[PDB]
Image (spheres, rainbow, N blue to C red):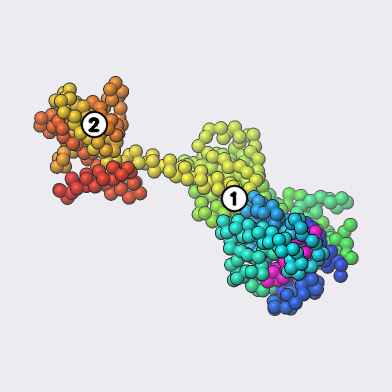
Amino acid sequence: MKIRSPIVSVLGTTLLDHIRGSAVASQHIGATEIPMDVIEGICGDFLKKFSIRETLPGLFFIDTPGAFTTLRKRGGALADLAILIVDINEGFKPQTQEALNILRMYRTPFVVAANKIDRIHGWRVHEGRPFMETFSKQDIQVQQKLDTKVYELVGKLHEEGFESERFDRVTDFASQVSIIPISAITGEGIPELLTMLMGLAQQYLREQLKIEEDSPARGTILEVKEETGLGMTIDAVIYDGILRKDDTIAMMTSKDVISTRIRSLLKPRPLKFQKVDEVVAAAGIKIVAPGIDDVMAGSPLRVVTDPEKVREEILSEIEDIKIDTDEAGVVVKADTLGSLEAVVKILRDMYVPIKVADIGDVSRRDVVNAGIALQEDRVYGAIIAFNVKVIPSAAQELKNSDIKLFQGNVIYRLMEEYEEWVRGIEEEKKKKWMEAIIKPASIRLIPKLVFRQSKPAIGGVEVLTGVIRQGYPLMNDDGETVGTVESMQDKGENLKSASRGQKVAMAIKDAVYGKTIHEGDTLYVDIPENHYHILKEQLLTDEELDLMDKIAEIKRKKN
């Protein structure tokens, strides 16, 4: 058993391009590894406070700015730590909220590198010096301008739910994000950037770094791409175990689990490719093997021991990111395995059930399924398609509304759009169910306006409070039943609903003037006990509320 190097993804590049020079100024495919001794050489005595430095090989940086979403293992992120790069002059942006969203979602410890400090008006570069050193040599007004921009970032982070501060002012390192102002182009601030990473390693990394350097290699494919001279190849990161040139490895394709016997393991040329016999966890490597081509970026990579065990172990990992059930509802489609897992994770996070989740453009069958799910709660009758096009065959068999389609290349916007969409469809529901509820309404029988005594009694009437509807039951001042609103007419208009001080000619079935009903009388809607109870959730105008209590008192004298 060994303790490997933490894997660090960079979100938001000359960062590693000048960091690579850091060490070279004394190789992995898709990654750069900075040995611990080099880190200590760059970080003065600032590191001497972190005891994990004596046990780590160094830091393994993934050369993949963001997919991070593609850098994933069973359960989530393959990265142990992460740097979120923000431009300190431009401040926040969209891709920054998308990254933050993803970082908290996967719960990965991270630091923010407030890049481009060299671009602040009046700043004087001090090549490769720690931030504190260079900052203290700047003019008082230049120092103030950097703190102003930093605090604007602290502000945005706060709106987003993260408390944070410039690294040297952080209180409680576990909950505040540490912001390290830097300049990638210059080496300014890089020392503290690395010290805060060693800082996060000290705070959160233990058993996650333990590997069994002899066990069959556990990795993840980040790129399936052609290469001159060696057709299709695979670039992978190994996080546990050992991979050998003669190994057999299984991986997921878009349809099935396959395996291939490796022909070559290639890495960059030391200090185009260089062949190697093996690689140990904490490695980025290019693989040359036969039946790849349809291999999925983001798929697990496993050297094969037992074909049955490896096969189902891979199948189950993917089973969680697919879902093709019948129940629930909501269809999700992303352009990649990682994205898909991110979206499904966020949705699954919002307890929103899913019926479909897969890769590829929206298809007729996705629309059909959005329908089968629409048949129960139109809130599910939606298609959420992340960075994926809509096949013509489905853009037509989708014409019939009822199934909303959210498109976009940014995940939080789509989610925001979903939630609010659900909001309207959520209000445009109570309402629908409200109509079926008999609201409070009061009515006054205008004197000297009797057009008919019995049969429908018919008289001029004024709406006192609320809204009386055709069919509403009417009762006495003493709770006695009087009749039912048969029909209404305002001047020449036939109505079923009348409010305010409307005044109309009203036909009242079952009522009889100078008997059951009397001119001048005030009649009240005979709301049903149950309907009344539904005052909760369903709750009016300051009048309908006072009236509801009155109807209550009125009936109360009998219950």
Count of numbered tags: 2
Q: CA distance from mark 2 to mark 1?
A: 52 Å
Residue 169 screen position, x and y as percent: 64, 69
**Mark 1 nearby-residue class (10 Å; few <14, some 14–19, many ≥20):** some
497 drawn magenta: no
Question: Which residue appears at 16% of the width and 38% of the height?
Answer: 476
Counting from the top left corner in percent of width and height, residue 185 is at 80, 59
Amino acid carrying label 2: it is Glu
Residue 462 badge? 2
Give whichever of 20, 550 is nearer the camera. Answer: 550
- Residue 24, quarter of the rendered image: bottom right
541 or 454, which is in the foreground? Answer: 541
Q: Which residue is mark 1?
A: 412
Does 237 sit left or right of 485 as displayed? right
Does the magenta-highlighted stretch encompass residue 184? yes
Upstream in sequence: badge 2 or badge 1 = 1
Residue 456 visible (yes or no): no
Residue 540 left/right relative to 393: left
Q: Quadrant of residue 45?
A: bottom right
Per the rendered image, the range of residues in magenta is 181-200
Name the residue type under label 1: Tyr
Q: Depth-wise, is mark 2 or mark 1 nearer the camera?
A: 2
Q: Residue at x 23, y 31 (%)?
A: 462
Q: Which residue extends farthest front?
A: 140
- Residue under the point 63% across and 38% down: 390
